[PDB]
Structures are given as structure tokens and as C-alpha cells.
Length: 165
Ligand SMILES: CS(=O)(=O)NCC1CCNCC1
Image (cartoon, rainbow, N blue to C red; front, side, top):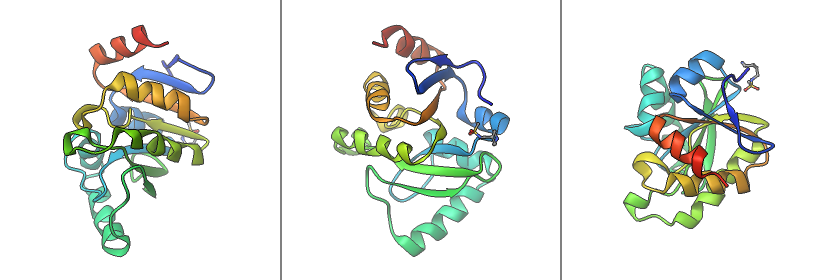
């Protein structure tokens, strides 16, 4: 199972790790992708997860969008986890760099509650532009299922742990 995580709460755990490497190692039931409404996995966590699938995630995602249309900001869909996990839960957190409402971050994290255990990044963090300290607080106050957070940046991981209330 998951190794080397620091326990933050009864159900939230955190580790300084590359989520692709973490997924390839653990092969969790669910890996969360920091998706956008179009499932265009260009950069950030989405670009990295997609590249690890040799673009199979993008091919599957384009078929999903052609059939269903775009996701809502705060919404999600379950697709294959390919070589990373049994499933990938593509969750759309608000992108404050595209002027999206930060209030949607709680709705985005609520998607995690449909899965008993997940390997995930901090939603809306990184290139999505939100404060990762705020994202972690919304995560621990919203998610009730077991979430293993992978934070790529060591300096950000240290800041998150040292400022965790
Ligand atoms: C760690 S998890 O609860 O996400 N998955 C359970 C098993 C162990 C890891 N490989 C898949 C089977």
C-alpha cells in the first residue's frame, strides 16, 4: 500500500512525491487527475499523467468529450487509470488563472468522497493558480474518504506541513 506519508488528519495523508512515480509504484484503485473541463491534458499534473500513459489517457479523454461534452468546473468523471491506476478520477478544480471561482474548490473535492481511497494532487494548485495552503485546508475540511496527497515540490511540501493547522 502507500508508504512514507505524513498523517495530517484521520483520513488525509501527504507526501513529497511525483504523483506519476507514486502511481506507477502503488497502482492505486484511483489516481486523481487535475483535469480541465475539456480533458485536454497539456501541462501540470494532467500533462505528466497523460505523458506517462503514452497519450492513451488523452485518446480516451477525447472520445469521452466527443460523446459527453465538457465537464463542469467542480465536476469529475471516472475513466481508465491505464498503466497508473485501476481508474483515473478526472476532477476539475477552478483555474484562478482563467478567472474561475475559487468557491468551486469545495465542490471539486466532494468528488473524492465517492471513492474509498485515492492518490491525488492538491486541486487548483500549481498552474491552476490557487493557494495550495488553501487547497489543503479545503481538502481536509471536505474529503471524508482516505486521500493520499502527492506534492511534487519539496519546498511547497515543507511549507504545507509546517503551516498545517
Ligand atoms: C492502495 S488502494 O487501496 O488504492 N488499492 C488497493 C490494492 C493495492 C494497490 N494496488 C491496487 C489494489
